[PDB]
Length: 209
Image 1 (tube, rainbow, N blue to C red):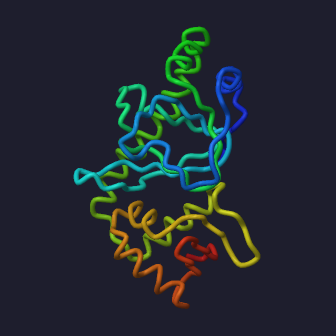
Image 2 (spheres, one colour):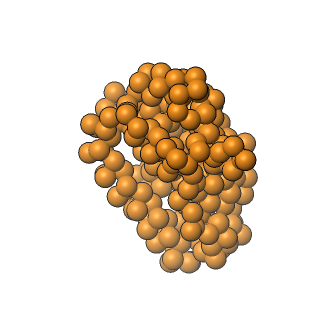
């Protein structure tokens, strides 16, 4: 989405108390059914917002970047059984502490909780908007629109060929509100010299849809 600072002063007052580190992608941080406990500030990288369906199916609906706030839907409600919220899409490092340490630094610095609740609230608006589109949203070309939307994310790295987006067919399946099946089949056809240069575990779009 861009336009978002990683070195936010309010974070720095959190970071003096927090452990900054994480993993080169792969590690789901709120999505399993595991004690959240610790709050995560994206100080580096880019992740993908995913909630569980009525059947419990993981589905991507939005993206987070360096400057966004993770851990909210683990500690605010005190779920402590990490339903879903976020998945490490690309190499990300996050600011980590138990929510007690956090609530202390919001009681001494009142702004921190407002930073958390504001940035997260905006995400609540985007998903409330997605749950009445994705429920009907057809796959034809709408996958390509999503793939162009990814070209505004820091997880997409530019090459002399196209935008090297570090995703997979599940992700795009869920953002378009389809399955891994419909979107998977089509992305296979695209890398079969039809449309854009898919690679299964990567997508390369040329910008031209």
